[PDB]
Image (cartoon, chains in turn brown, orange):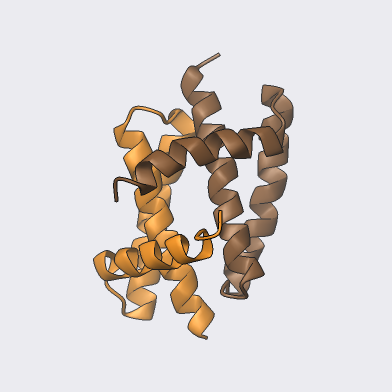
Length: 72
Length: 71
């Protein structure tokens, strides 16, 4: 198991949450919302393959992305 | 649509976040493929909208920090 595959999934799960937050705030346009729906299905598939819970991976992704954001 | 501008700004910033992670050697091959393909799409979107990516990226940072401010 490539450790980068796990980190990539965790990051993608958190970035999905960020985008969902944009949608919740009614700031996503129609194509943005379609990417959001389609990517959710994609992440579900990836999580299944990896044996990783999406919510758990999202939290892990948050910690990874938080360290990028704090250095911005 | 103003949401088209906001969506582009957020997408630019999130691409930058993904690039940062790739720079940190955290990306696998599909992650890197997506980063590279998406850079081309964002450049296309920037042309369609007449918006500079650098500027939209900074605006995106502000939107993201604002929508995550309570988290």
